[PDB]
Length: 12
Image (cartoon, rainbow, N blue to C red; front, side, top):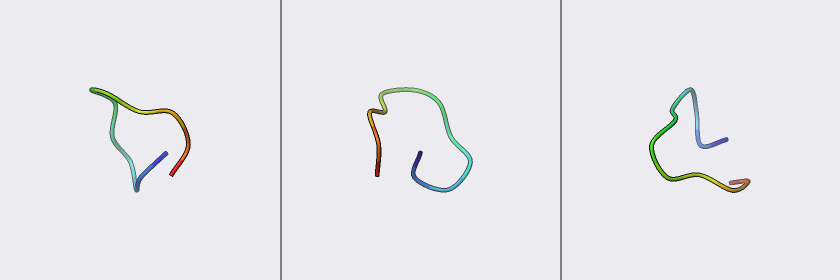
């Protein structure tokens, strides 16, 4: 999760 975001994510 890069910060707090959900569009295209795996584990960052």
